[PDB]
């Protein structure tokens, strides 16, 4: 468990480790918006 | 013709696929077929 | 300008998906075989034919869904929707395995429609028909495995069911019952498939690494133009490379590309011939000379003898649940087991 | 303090969300940029001051 | 020039009928050592106690095998991962009993086949080619490392390496499925897609090029004489082939860039075989294929069997029967 | 180049998304309701999780008779009550 | 836009990071931002792991891989690996997660806002890849940094609480290391050991004094080599041996990382000293040995004479000899007789497993440990069903050792592939044929035919 | 709770791109 | 066995030293284009 004061950020903590994977995907979004030049 | 940018269409459609497959992976652990 | 010629004009119009006369056969049959498979794996059980759940609706996943074969008691019945078994009841037809024959028969006629499409398009554009000829191999495989194999056997029940894990069961059934890995026709198939993937890998890699510098970019795909007359890669350098690495090399590009047709196509044909034998249980199950020796000399052991014991385990441990029409009751004391496990 | 901790932590969550969006949109818009460096300098130092606030108030709340 | 400079020029000479090179000075002795030992072992080696249980398996032709059943049997389970060269044995007869030839062959082979990869880099460099044929070869190479070395390491014994024979290969495969459910592992499934697709693409590319060959010959001669070695002109009409295959499927499904097409032919079976090799090499650490045994349960709690449950019965039959005298305790742990 | 309108012109147009922001959810919702009303079970004959077995049954309702298979299933279903 | 399309830069979008080869400011931003990703994951994963962490279950039953690293460093654990204080795990996660914002800010700054190249801004920070003396200087700075990092592990072990010692007398416990092994015949003796069975190369390190003393040697070697590379330029034999380019230095690192990845895979699979079994679960060898022990204990309790029981083959059912005469457990676990573990070593004598100690001196804590390890073998399915492939669903278990070994084999392999890709390309690009054969001077046409 | 955090995080990336697309940013 | 061990050690060392010194012997300059 987190220290009990932090217990409302548990839904945020549950999704924090996947955030790096979204950076990989974000490079494809940015390249789509410039049209892969 | 060229209203909505194709990158926006691609991104929302790409994310729609992720959500649907992610639901199917969620259903592997809940309900029918979960072994529970 | 009769009605035939105007219909021929429309069927052969340049469009996004070419239709053709073959498309009259191909497009409904392919759509139904594809759609029947998705329908059955989404919504249809195998509870009454196999005692299995086989649909997403019952809790299976993509690896475990299948459109399963009909019950063994159906024999080789066509299982038409209007036939004497379903009697026009769609719900019962799905329960009796009528979707299996539906997919198999429409898949068969679609595959014909696809090879007819290959001939028709090759004739219209003016190329030779080698792609259709190469497609004879997947057709030969489909016909031998999905039709001739169950026709030789007791019923359609023993055909492969159209599902991922169901196919895996078919693979392990053929080991345990047919010793199919020992069959020289399967071995020729393996060589054609693996030799085909090797040629695919090596030819692709050889072309990509003997390319001429035809432009300034470090990404080299832009330096190709389809209207060029010149070879895009150096056959001479490729030949010298492979002759020095491996001893032999291609020196004729036409023979190279034919050999690439020939290898996987011959392999698949060879495996089809093996499966036709297995339709009649004409297996390469055993080597008689080793069995004579192993029977009389309890110290003679080989990898072949070990595999036969594995096969005996497969048959005994799988048959009661894999063949529920037989009503096998194999008491625990009759099941072959080694020590401890 | 009790309510001061999570409120300042929910401030740090909120402000990080304005910094995660607002910093690359302001670094990649070099036109009206002199007006954006101040909000970057402010938000950076405000963010660092909230980490220290959450870090100090953790040891009255845990 | 001194003798060393002359020797180096011979070694790296592009005029040698077979290229030696620096990788070749390792590859050649190692591969000759592995070949000679393999051939002698396959013909003539006495039975080998593979399972460490004093139950020797006959692998050679002279001891009763044919081409199909014969093998070089893996080294003894009692040896484990221990290095067993000839000098560690008290005699050749003991080395033979314990499966010494297997360790000698696979070690020389893997060292030799690694240098074959390096040698492919080396010659491409000497010839001015691009360097990545060796990357393609790293797929079957990794596969060989997987079955001969990585699998034994994770399992703790060279007795679990794939035997050097045809039926021995099948035994390795069946036991592997029993213990790891390899068919239900997505890396193996990608391997299958790699090899079926590779054979498919091999057939497709062969057939489309052959279909679009430009007429240079008559009916009474092989069309292959229409191509001359080192001719500058293209021997097939890639626009015709694209025009066929883009009407067979649809236009944007078909390659019109030959460079893209050939890259795809490289990348598809290579990436697929890499996944296959990683499959074996990760099942070496007993991360197994998907287990859906009893995944489907009714409202009461009755197990409803699926096709995965039928696979498990077959898996059980191999498992209870394999190495039938080697197990003393209820769980097969390595 | 076969004369059809390009796909990237269609799916970037607003008229497409006027239409398909209605037709795509309606199809998805129609599929959702085919399951959640239970119609999928009655069209296909797939067992619900409480209709595989009778309450004390352990045996499988396997079809054993070719020309009376339609009746064997109906007798198996009438034993579910 | 500078070098941000294929026509200007020569590289397509999918080779887009190769446009940064000579843009040192944007390239610095790529690296700092990526370091932020690593630090983010370390932080975010730890907090995820801690939010899920049940203190009353073992860590290896919980799918944790970072919390065991922290526990091994001495934080949060009492005797036998039990968790006494979750708060050090919270700190390690938080401080990583906050520092990732700082690295992310500086990565994004240099990637998008700052100068594209550094060579005009600063002579110290700018570099040419072809500048061999500058390259060794940056290498030397980074060696000194890594050498201090190794000494930090020594600092924790010796002066800041110690490390978890699974081999400590009386059970595993956090122990300050007072006498690290400084003697180079021991430290560099591990480098010369065979990697094969019974030997294990550096993977067989089995005491924290050798671990700590090695890190003293590595920290001082890395600082000395750091200073050496700041003060020297690559000698003549080194300049003629290597390719001196950005892609070439990347390839050399990829070769190094692949080798290290393969070594870590073996470390986590076999070593129970720096990967304590109380945190990571039993090793593959450990569980198989634990099974033989469990059934030895049960059968001896029933009255069996375990040293004289024949198995089906004639070898001893519970006990047999290794190929060098040591008394070892029988059955298939004969392959794992070189396993050493703190629960098993009290039964070992001079000749291996002592039969009198086995009859009389197995404690209940060893019986519990053997049963626990036998039932937590690193065998499980990809959907985390524990046990063999034939097992039913019930147990949700895949050992951290399996997760860590499999992942790092996969990564080490592709990094080997990357090494081969980049080493071949850097060779070709330096010699000038990476874009293809020049049609006018095709090299093979100037060669004599082979036959 | 978990589904709304991943939604707000999952839109922040595309919003950066969309906001620089509308201000003619240095993409 | 000892004589065989020494013979293999010598032979293996010989070929390894050929490989290492041979790659040290100006290997990047053995190419058809830039003989620097
Ligand atoms: C080419 C490329 C293009 C491919 C074309 C695409 C596919 C086209 C469509 C194919 C559909 C084929 C369906 C054939 C069904 C079949 O056969 O159905 C089988 C029936 C015979 O019925 C079977 O008959 C058996 C024998 O019974 C007999 O014996 C019993 C025991 O004594 C009883 O006496 C019984 O009353 C008596 O009839 C059992 O009863 C089986 O259950 C029952 O299924 O034959 C019949 O319909 C017809 C038999 C004669 C025609 C056979 C030609 C086709 C088969 C070729 C393959 C031969 C395979 C040999 C394997 C090698
Ligand atoms: C460039 C130069 C490199 C190439 C030049 C040629 C180099 C030759 C290297 C020889 C490596 C032989 C492979 C055997 C590795 C092995 O048995 O590995 C295992 C060993 C560890 O060995 C084990 O180590 C154990 C140590 O544990 C002991 O100590 C522990 C202390 O905690 C515990 O107490 C434990 O219980 C106790 O038993 C025991 O000794 C075991 O018996 C022993 O088996 O790892 C090791 O030494 C660590 C290194 C293993 C590397 C893994 C290689 C992977 C390569 C993949 C290549 C893919 C290629 C693709 C091509 C395309
Ligand atoms: C770890 C992953 C990683 C990193 C750090 C980079 C970094 C970089 N890439 Mg590369 N790239 C990557 C993966 C990565 N890339 C992948 C996976 C692909 C394939 C799609 C590419 C394909 C590619 C191409 C084709 C190009 C680059 C280019 C670049 C450089 C400049 C980008 C730019 O200015 O555009 C501007 C983009 C924006 C302004 C959009 C805003 C995006 C921001 C940065 C996101 C940050 C959000 C984050 C949550 C906020 C943190 C703030 C907080 C810490 C305060 C930059 C150094 C370019 C280059 O090399 O030019 C010389 C270039 O042309 N990349
Ligand atoms: C690999 C790491 C790295 C490197 C080599 C650089 C290099 C550079 N930075 Mg960048 N930067 C970085 C990371 C890095 N930075 C990070 C993490 C941030 C966010 C804080 C920034 C934010 C930043 C800004 C806003 C600016 C620079 C600038 C510069 C240039 C001049 C810096 C200088 O002379 O200060 C002299 C350095 C010192 C007096 C000492 C450094 C101060 C810190 C506090 C010491 C920390 C050292 C310690 C070992 C760190 C351990 C980190 C570890 C845990 C990861 C130089 C090219 C300037 C520039 O771009 O000019 C145009 C500039 O304006 N950087
Ligand atoms: C990241 C770490 C790192 C890197 C990249 C470098 C890189 C370099 N070093 Mg430096 N060095 C380092 C750390 C490092 N060093 C440290 C920590 C020290 C102090 C120990 C030194 C002390 C040092 C000296 C004294 C010299 C270098 C030199 C060099 C240059 C050439 C090296 C070479 O040819 O390698 C390849 C090595 C060889 C060809 C030697 C034979 C290697 C055999 C064939 C393989 C043996 C290992 C094998 C895999 C077995 C491993 C296990 C084994 C222990 C049992 C190169 C720039 C040379 C230079 O030019 O400096 C100016 C040089 O003279 N370094
Ligand atoms: C430190 C490690 C490292 C670094 C700095 C580089 C750097 C580079 N590589 Mg190399 N590479 C590496 C490791 C590395 N590589 C490894 C390990 C391999 C073997 C796989 C390669 C194989 C490789 C090839 C084949 C090529 C490069 C190329 C390049 C250049 C451009 C890269 C780019 O823009 O990609 C942009 C990024 C993408 C297009 C996305 C890639 C996505 C991958 C394939 C899947 C992602 C993995 C993920 C876990 C799975 C999906 C998860 C899902 C949930 C989304 C750049 C110099 C190119 C080059 O040679 O330039 C000269 C090139 O053609 N690299
Ligand atoms: C990453 C894996 C690497 C992909 C390439 C592997 C094939 C090697 C075949 C033998 C060499 C064949 C050969 O020589 O290739 C050469 C070919 C073209 O070479 P060029 O020199 O034109 O470009 C490569 C570099 O020079 C950069 O410009 O290389 C490329 O196409 C690289 C593509 C990288 C594309 C980015 C990586 C993403 C692809 C992988 C995604 C896979 C999805 C998997 C899902 C399961
Ligand atoms: C049988 C029958 C019929 C028919 C029907 C039909 C025709 C159907 C169709 C149907 C269909 C037509 C369906 C569809 C379905 C689909 C689906 C269900 C899909 C799915 C998808 C997904 C899931 C995705 C995924 C993926 C992949 C695949 C790959 C890539 C990646 C991803 C992930 C994206 C009739 C009435 C005539 C008659 C009687 C019988
Ligand atoms: C350049 C580039 C790129 C990249 C990017 C990157 C790589 C970045 C990074 C970034 C980063 C790396 C970032 C970071 C961030 C962080 C953050 C933002 C933090 C936060 C923190 C906080 C706020 C927390 C809180 C808390 C606490 C304190 C306690 C516990 C609880 C919690 C968790 C709540 C790309 C590819 C896209 C493309 C283009 C270019
Ligand atoms: C910490 C520790 C320790 C220690 C350790 C040590 C002390 C280490 C060292 C290490 C080292 C001391 C390493 C080294 C490495 C090396 C390498 C890995 C090498 C490489 C090389 C190469 C790469 C080369 C190449 C080449 C050739 C061959 C020819 C010519 C060209 C070239 C140059 C390219 C111990 C175990 C006690 C315990 C645990 C912890
Ligand atoms: C720690 C923390 C934080 C931070 C966070 C962050 C750092 C974020 C990031 C985020 C991001 C970084 C995101 C991103 C996203 C992305 C996405 C969403 C993408 C997607 C994609 C897709 C879907 C794709 C598609 C496509 C295209 C585009 C083209 C080609 C094709 C395809 C279809 C593939 C905050 C502030 C909250 C506070 C609390 C704590
Ligand atoms: C593994 C144990 C050995 C470790 C070796 C590390 C020692 C470091 C210094 C070794 C010196 C290598 O130095 C290298 O020697 C060779 C042969 O003598 C030199 O001489 C070479 O000249 C040219 C290329 O330059 C070649 O065509 C020629 O065949 C060769 O004689 C190289 O130009 C020099 O770079
Ligand atoms: Cl066996
Ligand atoms: Cl056992
Ligand atoms: Fe070709
Ligand atoms: Mg479910």
Image (tube, coloured by chain):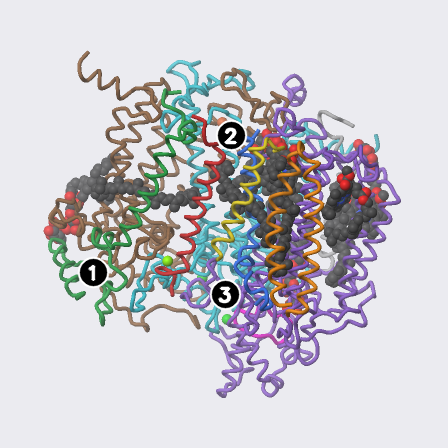
Chain colours: A blue, B red, C brown, D orange, E cyan, F green, G purple, H yellow
Quarter of the image with the C terminus of chain G is top right
Q: Is residue C51 left or right of residue C131?
A: left
Q: Which residue is mark 1?
A: F62
On whether residue D23 falls in the magenta region, the answer is no
Q: Is residue E218 left or right of residue G141?
A: left
Q: Position of residue E251 (x, y in %)?
A: 40, 25
Q: Residues within 10 Å of mark 3 (few under 14, many from 20)?
A: many
Comparing labels 3 and 1, the label whose residue is closer to the camera: 3
Q: Nearer the viewer, residue C215 or G58?
A: G58
Q: Secondary structure at mark 2?
A: helix
Q: Is residue I18 above or below residue G296?
A: above
Q: Is residue C327 left or right of residue G289?
A: left
Q: Is residue C38 above or below residue G428?
A: below
Ligand 15 is within 8 Å of the C-beta of the residue at disc 2: yes
Q: Which residue is mark 2?
A: E262
Question: Disc 1 versus disc 2: distance between alpha carbons?
Answer: 52 Å
Q: Chain of mark 2?
A: E
Q: Which residue is mark 3?
A: G397
Q: Position of residue I6 (x, y in %)?
A: 75, 55
- In the rendered image, the residue lying farthest to the top is C1
Q: Are marks 3 and 1 in contact (CB under 8 Å)?
A: no
Q: Secondary structure at mark 3?
A: loop
Question: Start and end of the magenta stretch?
Answer: G325-340
Image quadrant of residue C29?
top left
Q: Chain of mark 1?
A: F
Q: Mark 3 and mark 1, same subunit?
A: no
User: For the point 65% across and 21% down, which residue is it?
Assistant: G438
Q: Nearer the viewer, residue C271 or C22?
A: C22
Q: Is residue C140 left or right of residue A11?
A: left
């Amino acid at each position: 468990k987190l220290p009990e004061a932090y217990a409302i950020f548990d839904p945020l903590v549950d999704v924090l480790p996947v955030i790096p994977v979204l950076f990989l995907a974000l490079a494809f979004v940015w390249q789509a918006a410039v049209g892969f030049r | 013709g060229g209203r909505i940018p194709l990158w926006i269409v691609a991104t929302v459609a790409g994310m729609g696929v992720i959500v649907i497959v992610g639901l199917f992976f969620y259903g592997a652990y809940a309900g029918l077929g979960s072994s529970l | 300008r009769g009605w035939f010629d105007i219909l021929d004009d429309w069927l052969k119009r340049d469009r996004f998906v070419f239709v053709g006369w073959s498309g009259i056969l191909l497009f409904p049959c392919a759509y139904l075989a594809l759609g029947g498979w998705l329908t059955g794996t989404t919504f249809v059980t195998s509870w009454y034919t196999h005692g299995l759940a086989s649909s997403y609706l019952e809790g299976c996943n993509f690896l475990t869904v299948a459109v399963s074969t009909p019950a063994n008691s159906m024999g080789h019945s066509l299982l038409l929707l209007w036939g004497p078994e379903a009697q026009g009841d769609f719900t019962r037809w799905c329960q009796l395995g009528g979707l299996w024959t539906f997919i198999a028969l429409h898949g068969a006629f679609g595959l014909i429609g696809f090879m007819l499409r290959q001939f028709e398009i090759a004739r219209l554009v003016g190329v030779r028909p080698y792609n259709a000829i190469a497609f004879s191999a997947p057709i030969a495989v489909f016909v031998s495995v999905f039709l001739i194999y169950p026709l030789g056997q007791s019923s359609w029940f023993f055909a492969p069911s159209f599902g991922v894990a169901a196919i895996f069961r078919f693979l392990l059934f053929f080991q345990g019952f047919h010793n199919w890995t020992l069959n020289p026709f399967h071995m020729m198939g393996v060589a054609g498939v693996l030799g085909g993937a090797l040629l695919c890998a090596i030819h692709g890699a050889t072309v990509e690494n003997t390319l001429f510098q035809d432009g300034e970019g470090a990404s080299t795909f832009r330096a190709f133009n389809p209207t060029q007359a010149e070879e895009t890669y150096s056959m001479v350098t490729a030949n010298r490379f492979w002759s020095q690495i491996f001893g032999i090399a291609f020196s004729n590009k036409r023979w190279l590309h034919f050999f690439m047709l020939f290898v996987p196509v011959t392999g698949l044909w060879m495996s089809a011939i093996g499966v036709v034998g297995l339709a009649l249980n004409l297996r390469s199950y055993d080597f008689i000379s080793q069995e004579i020796r192993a029977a009389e000399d309890p110290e003679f052991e080989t990898f072949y003898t070990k595999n036969l014991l594995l096969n005996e385990g497969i048959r005994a441990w799988m048959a009661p649940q894999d063949q529920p029409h037989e009503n096998f009751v194999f008491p625990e004391e009759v099941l072959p087991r080694g020590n401890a496990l | 303090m009790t309510i001061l901790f999570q409120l300042a932590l929910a401030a740090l969550v909120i402000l990080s969300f304005v910094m995660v969006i607002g910093v690359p949109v302001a670094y990649a818009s070099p036109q009206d940029w002199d007006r954006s460096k101040q909000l970057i300098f402010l938000g950076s130092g405000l963010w660092i001051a909230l980490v220290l606030v959450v870090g100090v108030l953790n040891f009255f709340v845990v | 020039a001194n003798l060393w400079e002359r020797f180096c020029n011979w070694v790296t000479s592009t005029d040698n009928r077979l290229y030696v090179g620096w990788f070749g000075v390792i590859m050649i002795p190692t591969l000759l050592a592995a070949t000679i030992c393999f051939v002698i072992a396959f013909i003539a080696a006495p039975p080998v106690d593979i399972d460490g249980i004093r139950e020797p398996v006959s692998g050679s032709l002279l001891y009763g095998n044919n081409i199909i059943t014969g093998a070089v049997v893996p080294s003894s389970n009692a040896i484990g991962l221990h290095f067993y060269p000839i000098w560690e044995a008290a005699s050749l007869d003991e080395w033979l009993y314990n499966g010494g030839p297997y360790q000698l062959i696979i070690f020389h082979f893997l060292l030799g086949a690694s240098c074959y990869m390096g040698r492919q880099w080396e010659l491409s460099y000497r010839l001015g080619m691009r360097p990545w044929i060796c990357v393609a070869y790293s797929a079957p190479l990794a596969s060989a490392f997987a079955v001969f070395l990585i699998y034994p390491i994770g399992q703790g014994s060279f007795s679990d390496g794939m035997p050097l024979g045809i039926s021995g290969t099948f035994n390795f495969m069946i036991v592997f499925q029993a213990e790891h459910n390899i068919l239900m592992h997505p890396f193996h499934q990608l391997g299958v897609a790699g090899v079926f697709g590779g054979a498919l693409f091999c057939a497709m590319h062969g057939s489309l090029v052959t279909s679009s060959l430009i007429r240079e010959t008559t009916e009474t001669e092989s069309a292959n004489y229409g191509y001359k070695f080192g001719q500058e002109e293209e021997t097939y009409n890639i626009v015709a082939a694209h025009g066929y295959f883009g009407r067979l499927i649809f236009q944007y499904a078909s390659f019109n860039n030959s460079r893209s097409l050939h890259f795809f032919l490289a990348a598809w079976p290579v990436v697929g075989v890499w996944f296959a090799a990683l499959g074996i090499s990760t099942m070496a650490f007993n991360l197994n294929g998907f287990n859906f045994n009893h995944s489907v349960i009714d409202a009461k709690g009755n197990v409803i069997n699926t096709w995965a449950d039928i696979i498990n019965r077959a898996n059980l039959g191999m498992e209870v029967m394999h190495e039938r005298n080697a197990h003393n305790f209820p769980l097969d742990l390595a | 180049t076969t004369g059809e309108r390009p796909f990237s012109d269609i799916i970037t147009s607003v008229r497409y998304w006027v239409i398909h922001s209605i037709t795509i959810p309606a199809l998805f919702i129609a599929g959702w309701l085919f399951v959640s009303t239970g119609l999928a079970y009655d069209v296909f004959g797939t067992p619900r999780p409480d209709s595989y077995y009778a309450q004390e049954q352990r045996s499988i309702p396997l079809v054993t008779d070719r020309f009376e298979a339609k009746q064997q299933v109906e007798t198996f279903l009438e034993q579910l009550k | 836009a500078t070098n941000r399309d294929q026509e200007s830069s020569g590289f397509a979008w999918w080779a887009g990071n190769a446009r940064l080869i000579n843009l040192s400011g944007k390239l610095l931003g790529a690296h700092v931002a990526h370091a932020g990703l690593i630090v983010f994951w370390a932080g975010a994963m730890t907090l995820f792991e801690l939010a899920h962490f049940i203190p009353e279950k073992p860590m290896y039953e919980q799918g944790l891989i970072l919390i065991p690293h922290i526990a091994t460093l001495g934080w949060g654990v009492g005797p036998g690996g039990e968790v006494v204080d979750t708060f050090p795990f919270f700190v390690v996660g938080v401080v990583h997660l906050i520092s990732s914002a700082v690295l992310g800010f500086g990565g994004v700054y240099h990637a998008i806002r700052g100068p594209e190249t550094l060579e005009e801004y600063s002579s110290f920070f700018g570099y040419d890849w072809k500048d061999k003396n500058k390259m060794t200087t940056i290498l030397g700075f980074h060696l000194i940094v890594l050498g201090i990092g190794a000494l930090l592990l020594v600092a924790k072990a010796m002066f800041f609480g110690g490390l978890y010692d699974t081999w400590a007398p009386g059970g595993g416990d956090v122990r300050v290391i007072t006498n690290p092994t400084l003697d180079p015949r021991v430290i560099f003796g591990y480098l010369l050991k065979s990697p094969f069975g019974g030997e294990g190369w550096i993977v067989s390190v089995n005491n924290l004094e050798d671990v700590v003393g090695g890190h003293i040697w590595i920290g001082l070697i890395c600082i000395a080599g750091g200073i050496w590379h700041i003060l020297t330029t690559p000698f003549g034999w080194a300049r003629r041996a290597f390719i001196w380019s950005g892609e070439a230095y990347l390839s050399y690192s990829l070769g190094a990382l692949s080798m290290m990845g393969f070594i870590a895979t073996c470390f986590v699979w076999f070593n129970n000293t720096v990967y304590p079994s109380e945190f990571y679960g039993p090793t593959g060898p450990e569980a198989s040995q634990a099974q033989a022990m469990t059934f030895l204990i049960r059968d001896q309790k029933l009255g069996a004479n375990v040293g004289s029981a024949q198995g089906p083959t004639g070898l001893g059912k519970y006990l047999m000899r290794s190929p060098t005469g040591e008394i070892i457990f029988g059955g298939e676990t004969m392959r794992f007789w070189d396993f050493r573990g703190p629960w098993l070593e009290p039964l070992r004598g001079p000749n291996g497993l002592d039969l009198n100690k086995i009859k009389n001196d197995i404690q209940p804590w060893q019986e519990r440990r053997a049963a626990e390890y036998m039932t937590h073998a690193p065998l499980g399915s990809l959907n985390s069903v524990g046990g063999v492939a034939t097992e039913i669903n019930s147990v949700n278990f895949v050992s951290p050792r399996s997760w860590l070994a499999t992942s790092h084999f996969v990564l080490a392999f592709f990094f080997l592939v990357g090494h081969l890709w980049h080493a071949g390309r850097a060779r070709a690009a330096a010699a000038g044929f990476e874009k293809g054969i020049d049609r006018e001077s095709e090299p093979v046409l100037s060669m004599p035919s082979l036959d | 709770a978990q589904l709304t955090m991943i939604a707000m995080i999952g839109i922040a990336g595309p919003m950066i791109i969309f906001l620089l697309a509308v201000r003619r940013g240095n993409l | 066995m000892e004589t065989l061990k020494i013979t293999v050690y010598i032979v293996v060392t010989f070929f390894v030293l050929l490989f290492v010194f041979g790659f040290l012997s100006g290997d990047p300059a053995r190419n058809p284009k830039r003989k620097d």
